[PDB]
Length: 354
Image (tube, rainbow, N blue to C red):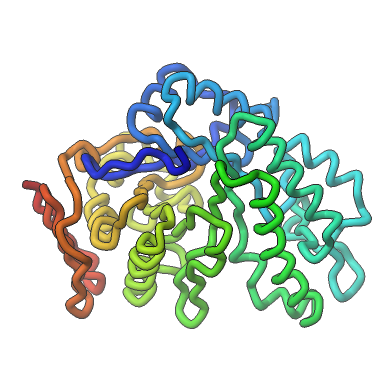
C-alpha cells in the first residue's frame, strides 16, 4: 500500500520526532505503533550512530511491530547538519558549497551551512542520500524540509536575483530528481504550508509530492486569525487534491523555545497541554480531510511531549458528514460521532462528542 492506512475511527494522528540519545525502547515503540501508522523520524534520531543508521534501525523495529506503518526519513533540502554520516561527505566537497554575493560561504549558523540547490552536482549527491535511505533502506519515504527558508526573499540580498531564481528552480528539480530516484512506491513529505500575513506559502510543490506539512498552526508568526484560517483552508484544499496533510499543533503557543514553559515540571507542562488541546484539535477537525493527520506536542524531540496522550484522541470520531462551514471567524464541521465548533477570533472552541 502507498499511503499509511487511514481511519476516522479516532482522531487521525501522526508522529514527528527524534530521540536524540538513542533508539526507542520496546515500550516507546508500542506506544507509537499502537497510536499511528505514520511516523516521521527527525535529524538526530538514534543517538551517536547518527541519523542514517538510527532511522534505518528504527524503521525495522517499527515495522517489526506494525508492518503497515510508514516510516519517513528526514533529509533537509537546504541545511547541512552535523547529525548524519552524510555530513562528513559534504564537508569533503567544498566545490559544492553555496557562496554569497560577497564571496564568503553561506552559513545559516556557524555549524549549519546552506546548500546550493542550483548546483546539479550537489543535488545528485543529496538525492543519493535519500535514495540509499529509502530504496536501499527501511524507510518508506523522505521528508524534505526547509522549503520555506529556500524561498525567503531575504536571500536575494545575499545571493542576487539571478542566483536566487536558479536556486528556486533547483528546488523544484531536487524534488523531481528525488521522485525519479525513489520510484513510485515511496513517499515524499515536504514542509511548506506556512501562513504569514502578506507572505503566505501554500501547497506550492504538488506534482511529485504526497504529503505537505503545516508546521506552525496558531504559533510563531502564524498566530493571527487570518493565518489560522489560511492554514485550515490550505489543509482542506490540499487534502481534497488527495495529499496527505500533517497538521502540527502546539499547546497554547508553548514550545521548546519557550523557556518559561520548558522550565516548568513535567506534571505542569502536561496539565497545560491537556487543557489547551481543544482549540487546535477543533481547528484540525474543522478542515481535516482523508489522510489528514494531527500532531500535538511542544517540540520535535521525542520527549517534547511526543509520547503524551490525551482522552480526546481516544474518543470515537467517525467519518465527516459535511464540508467545513465558514461563518466569518467561526468554523464548524460534523462527524458521525462529533460536532466541531471554534471561533478563530476568540480562540475558543467546543467539540461535542456523541
